[PDB]
Image (cartoon, rainbow, N blue to C red):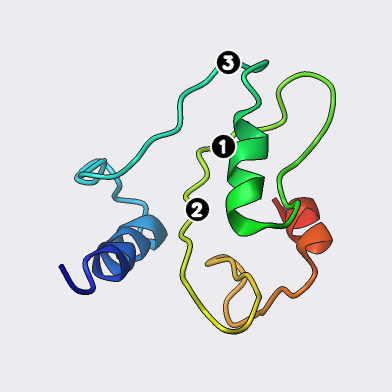
Amino acid sequence: MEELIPLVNRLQDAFSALGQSCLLELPQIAVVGGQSAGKSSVLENFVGRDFLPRGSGIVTRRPLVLQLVTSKAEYAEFLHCKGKKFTDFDEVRLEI
């Protein structure tokens, strides 16, 4: 169809910021894998940049909603970082 993924992204974003995500958990993809499965590398190969935390033991302690949008430019933005544009993906991991 046309504009389904970006539309639901807006819905997810709208549901994300006003914490009432109990109504949510609506259709979307959830990533499940062992610590040794290397699921982090798969995601990093999608973006084409390293931006996920690395360290001994589990580093991901919060559910990460990763919304990928095709664009000519390359940057990232956090909802809790209103208006700020990240161009350094090494800064992105540190922010997470």
Comes first in the chain, label 2 or label 3? 3
Percent x, y for residue 31?
45, 32
Comes first in the chain, label 1 or label 3? 3
Report how many numbered discs are placed on residues in the image. Answer: 3
Q: Identity of the amino acid at label 2?
A: Leu
Residue at x 48% of width, y 73% of height:
70
Indicate whether 5 appears above or below 29: below
Q: Secondary structure at mark 1?
A: loop
Residue at x 77% of width, y 18% of height:
57
Q: Secondary structure at mark 3?
A: loop
Percent x, y for residue 69?
46, 69
Q: Which residue is mark 3?
A: 34
Indicate whether 93 appears above or below 88: above
Q: Label 2, label 1: how many angstroms apart (C-alpha)?
A: 12 Å
Q: Identity of the amino acid at label 3?
A: Gly
21 left or right of 32 in image: left
Image quadrant occupied by the N terminus: bottom left
Q: Residue furthest left?
A: 1
36 left or right of 88 in image: left
Q: Identity of the amino acid at label 1?
A: Arg
Which labelled disc corresponds to residue 35? none
Q: Which residue is mark 1?
A: 62
13 left or right of 81 in image: left
Q: Nearer the viewer, residue 27 or 20?
A: 27
Which labelled disc corresponds to residue 66? 2
Residue 56 quadrant? top right
Characterize the local packing of mark 3: few (<14), some (14-19) or many (20 or more) Cα atoms within 10 angstroms: few
Q: Label 2, label 3: how many angstroms apart (C-alpha)?
A: 19 Å
